Image: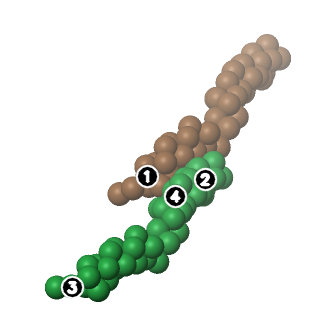
Chain colours: A brown, B green
């Protein structure tokens, strides 16, 4: 190999350092949203038993 | 040998002192021109790496 190849190697690692991956904060927000579901279903249950 | 031969020897040395040889300054200049080639290829390489 020669100088151009080696500079391209450096440039490629520079590219990978700035890659645009998916936004996983969206995934973690969807994980955090489950509190609302569980606690609202608990509200529903408690209301039904209270009415009964 | 005689006087004519000796004078011809002197004249031949006079001729050799003024012989017309190739112009070697052109060969020196062709040697010096290699800076441009090497440095322009380095410029090309660096431009390609920067683009990448």
The answer to whether residue B8 shows anywhere in this view is yes
Distance CA(mark 2)–CA(mark 4):
18 Å
Residue lying furthest left in this view?
B1
A40 up-or-down from B17: above or below? above
Residue at 60% of width from left, 53% of height from top?
A: B43
Asked whether the residues under marks 4 and 3 belong to the same chain, the reply is: yes
Q: What residue does disc 1 label? A: A3
Distance CA(mark 4)–CA(mark 1):
23 Å
Q: What residue does disc 2 label? A: B43
Chain letter for mark 1, please: A
Q: What residue does disc 4 label? A: B32
Residue at 51% of width from left, 65% of height from top?
A: B25
Counting other residues with Cα less than 10 Å from the Cα at mark 2, is it few (<14), some (14-19), or many (20 or more)?
A: few
Q: What residue does disc 3 label? A: B2
Choose the circle earlier in sequence order: 2 or 4. 4
Residue lying furthest front in this view?
B3
Left or right of B4 in this view: B45? right
Counting other residues with Cα less than 10 Å from the Cα at mark 1, is it few (<14), some (14-19), or many (20 or more)?
A: few
Circle 3: element type: loop
Residue A14 image-quadrant placement: top right
Residue at 45% of width from left, 73% of height from top?
A: B18
Circle 4: element type: helix
Circle 1: element type: helix
Is A48 or B49 nearer to us in this picture? B49
* Nearer to us: label 3 or label 2: 3
Asked whether the residues under marks 2 and 4 belong to the same chain, the reply is: yes
């Amino acid at each position: 190999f020669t100088l151009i190849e080696l500079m391209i190697v450096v440039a490629i690692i520079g590219i990978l350092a700035a890659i645009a991956i998916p936004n996983f904060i969206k995934f973690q927000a969807r994980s955090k949203q489950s509190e609302a579901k569980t606690n609202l279903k608990a509200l529903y249950t408690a209301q039904k038993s209270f009415f009964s």
